[PDB]
Length: 274
Ligand SMILES: O=C1NC(=O)/C(=C/c2cccc(C(F)(F)F)c2)S1
Image 1 (cartoon, rainbow, N blue to C red):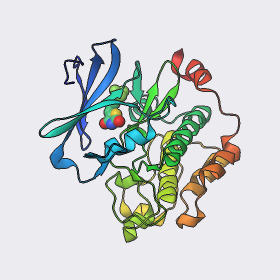
Image 2: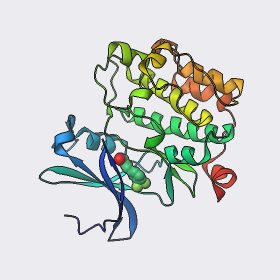
Image 3: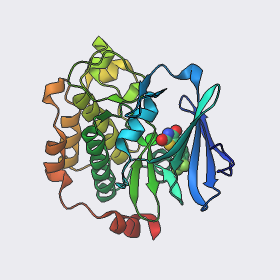
Image 4: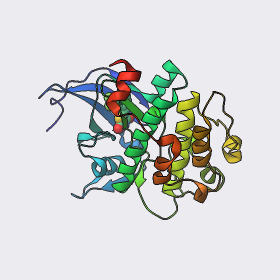
């Protein structure tokens, strides 16, 4: 037990998710990320198959661990008297999608197609494991720059998937749907689909469409960059004001704009410099 197992590197960041450090597992020099969450800031707890009391985040992360690389894998976790510490895999070299967009601005459609498809695959995997992420956005997406594989990260706002209404939310407001804003009610899939529309707009325009409650509620989308008609249509469909008017994951992936995606490795070659 205990961290003498890990050699702590530099702080990667800190925020509403806690404090995350670059690290290395001493027993094989495997890159990890070490994430400390304060007990005070955990509103949401569950219990595992094992059945002890842990943060919901840990429950959700265990439900999605697998060799499938589109979601971050929890390697281990530790309790401390005032915090939980989590050990997560860390690709290297790596860059989050927010920073990549800061650097390169609006993305070419072929590249956005490739990234967005990989995001769809990740989210379908989560829904499949009975998990609803509830904070899909560019800051929660890591790009493995060598392999061109994206990774969804940060389940600290997620919940067990269910088919009844959610009336609670602690993810990102500007990615949250009109129904959350107006009624504090949404269903899991359709709220997830709206945030995927925000995300895809973000990729192709270089920023999110809406900053204020009023704009979200209005749902009117203005394109500030040149974007093909097939792409604007997919976006405007993901951002239908009525939840039931939103596409399912399968309709998103059968959309004409989504055809002939590059493979992750082709993507890194053409676009990331491999
Ligand atoms: O599941 C997760 N929850 C978080 O807050 C994470 C932060 C993180 C931030 C930058 C880099 C990485 C790294 F994995 F690349 F290191 C991880 S990961």
